[PDB]
Length: 125
Image 1 (cartoon, rainbow, N blue to C red):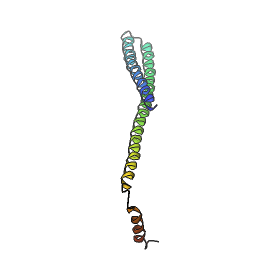
Image 2 (cartoon, rainbow, N blue to C red; image 1 turned 90 degrees about the vertical axis):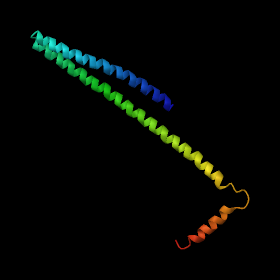
Image 3 (tube, helix red, strand yellow; image 1 turned 180 degrees about the vertical axis):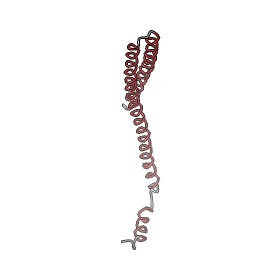
Image 4 (cartoon, one colour; image 1 turned 30 degrees about the vertical axis):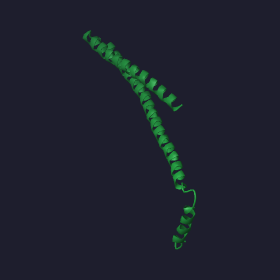
């Protein structure tokens, strides 16, 4: 159902959120490894650690892009459900106004209305 898709989007979103926390940790850790390589005067290994930092940041970007597509999909479903709730209310509402409109069981007033209606329009063409 629509509620089926909603719950799984949430579950997927929640898991991606933890991947994101994890990736930020590793980003930090690569930064700190680079500083330590420098205090040992190993300029090459520090650059290698910063390049690895760059790739994790790229992957964190992909994680957040997946999350964002899922949040938009969720919103689209919830809005569409609200729009459908309106349409069903309107349907049932129009049924109720039709019952009320013909709630005069004897003496057809509405046929006389349509007669007078056409007389009024007889300049229009």
